[PDB]
Image 1 (cartoon, protein in one colour):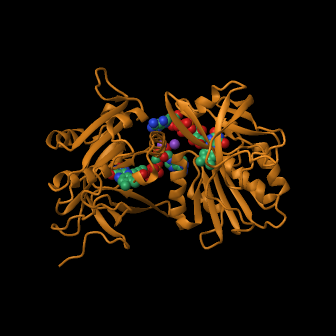
Image 2 (image 1 turned 60 degrees about the horizontal axis):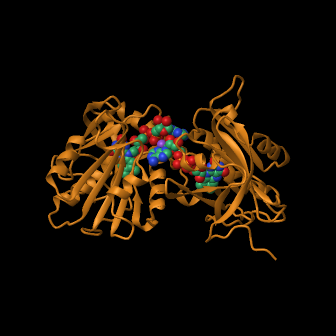
Image 3 (image 1 turned 30 degrees about the vertical axis):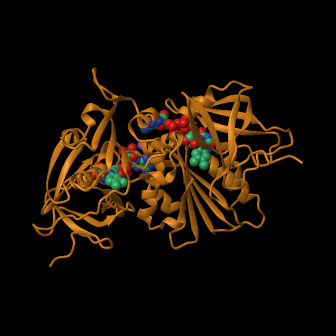
Length: 243
Length: 243
Ligand SMILES: Cc1cc2nc3c(=O)[nH]c(=O)nc-3n(C[C@H](O)[C@H](O)[C@H](O)COP(=O)(O)OP(=O)(O)OC[C@H]3O[C@@H](n4cnc5c(N)ncnc54)[C@H](O)[C@@H]3O)c2cc1C
Ligand SMILES: Cc1cc2nc3c(=O)[nH]c(=O)nc-3n(C[C@H](O)[C@H](O)[C@H](O)COP(=O)(O)OP(=O)(O)OC[C@H]3O[C@@H](n4cnc5c(N)ncnc54)[C@H](O)[C@@H]3O)c2cc1C
Ligand code: NA
Ligand code: NA
């Protein structure tokens, strides 16, 4: 009878199995777990913490796998690679057979079924991975009554990760809806245009007087601005959570 | 006997006296206090909160005046204007004679002389204003033995706000030192080059084993990266503060 895959105090090494190109700046990285029957086992709303040595110093970043909670023997990371981003460049230089050091689960989010009537999720870019993990857990549980509205914001149409997956979840589940926003939309776009606005949020989420938890993840200036909008709209800090 | 200039619970109106261009995207704005013998009255480490109405909705942002604590009958804000920055745009469209609504003081900082042996400050852009307010207070206190090391990072040489004032402080006070960092340095530059690195911080601040507080203010991606460095170098969360 085996240990859980991750330990919250001690880093373990996990080997890169394979990688593939998603778009110009994004790749999918598949790592082996230590046993074919292991699963990652992240609690809802929690993440992996990864460490690497770069120029003789250790660097640390959080990641949320996009493989579903129940996938056996491996986990998948979708990683956007930044021009001067130390860890995404480190991971994008690993070859099959190389290792990544990982501990967890980490994170202060504390999920209980039906903890709120409504979740408003705001995601930019790879901010979708923590949202996808929470949403999946909610919609696949048939006792959950939580309504989920996602505002998913990117620059260009080709930046919209997991569009097919999200579109399928929304077709299949009454309680999950997605609103897409693009700084540079194509002609005939039916979604949001520009940055996420206070109007877009007021139109799509229940107001402060309802039982709502708003969750955000994206680049730090997007998180900063969402918090400004939630202040504008009258939500209190107890009603939101930034990953 | 007059009331304090700011009230922490209620906004009051303060008139724009005049404005001046500092560089291509930065202006200095001078606001009248209600009586010529008033001072703005912000305790060390605290800020004012400004509100405005943009497209029917209230927005709110913090600012720290750059006028010294004892200036009578006005306060000065140096403000960088961003292309899609709602508040900085609002403020840059005010004419002399228009009002700005302000409340205060706001913030957690609680000055005690010699609360730490060393302060490491990291500022980017207008993140210098809260740092300047704290450093001015420390260096003018005879009892203070706190060593202050400031890393001040900007993109171009013309973006280094308050250089004259910072350098005069460093020459007068041996406990105050500044290291300037530029992404785009001029020919002959002897300061830091690029983004602020873990090594720049290690070379200028005392190690985690020391009695140190690190204070950061800057654009949100700079603050997120600085926190990455402080984790790399072994500082714990109780040893740092983001304004
Ligand atoms: C819960 C959670 C889950 C996440 N899940 C994923 C995921 O599944 N997939 C994914 O790709 N990401 C995910 N992220 C993001 C991840 O943690 C990292 O932030 C991301 O991988 C980029 O890290 P980096 O080291 O490559 O670049 P960063 O260090 O974050 O650099 C990014 C950019 O910032 C600027 N920059 C770099 N250094 C500095 C500096 N010294 N000063 C100022 N600016 C600087 C540069 O322009 C650089 O290109 C998640 C985050 C959280 C919180
Ligand atoms: C203690 C403290 C003191 C400060 N003192 C000063 C000071 O003296 N002077 C000063 O100038 N500033 C100061 N600041 C910062 C100030 O509070 C504001 O952050 C700043 O004025 C910019 O606000 P803004 O509304 O103009 O732009 P922001 O709303 O912050 O927009 C800035 C940029 O972010 C991007 N952006 C805008 N909206 C969104 C969105 N919806 N999603 C994603 N990205 C978006 C755009 O590129 C925009 O140009 C201080 C901050 C603190 C915490
Ligand atoms: Na950003
Ligand atoms: Na930024």
